[PDB]
Length: 99
Length: 99
Ligand SMILES: CC[C@H](C)CN(C[C@@H](O)[C@H](Cc1ccccc1)NC(=O)O[C@H]1CO[C@H]2OCC[C@H]21)S(=O)(=O)c1ccc(N)cc1
Image (cartoon, rainbow over the protein chains, first blue to last red):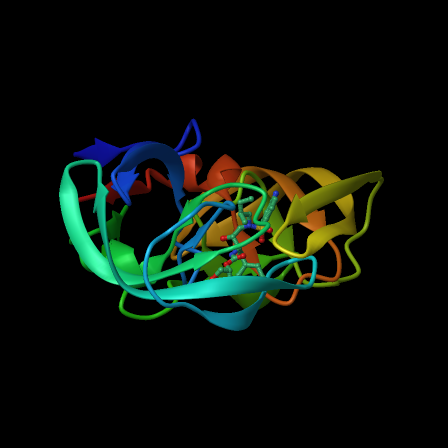
């Protein structure tokens, strides 16, 4: 679809068999989701945003469907203010900016 | 044009007579620029993201040119690590997400 930006570009995602709402965030290199349980191994990492750095759990090769489009990639889980879909997954679903 | 998301969507902007590089960020509600000495009145504001909040100065009806596309609206100024074009101005240049 074509998404205009007069509202937050929020979409429904499916991860770990659970539905959630997430923000399509072209300013995020990485995808960061709010606290949740995901199966499989994980490793501790740090990520920085506008206000500083947070501790997150890095999950690799995670299946995640974004607005009907499938992706498999890295998902960081931690105390982010909102679920954000970053470029590592936006590229997989063929997402571009157009003006 | 069309911008893919393999790399950060950085473009040249013109503000206050200065050329800068800024991120086209669908995840940012409002434009926030690195510290600069704009004239005029302003109002304090705090904006939150990953890591917490930063204090910024809100200027209204600031003219910005983004890739030859003119816009005018709110520009926040503060200690952001990156210049960020937010939705408040991305709408004014006709920018959409497409996949
Ligand atoms: C609450 C939604 C989202 C987190 C808001 N952010 C925009 C977002 O695009 C930032 C914009 C941003 C980019 C780079 C440094 C700091 C902020 N990106 C970001 O935090 O991404 C992180 C996850 O991937 C990594 O790549 C970038 C940092 C990591 S923000 O910077 O904090 C922001 C909040 C309010 C306004 N008006 C303008 C910007």
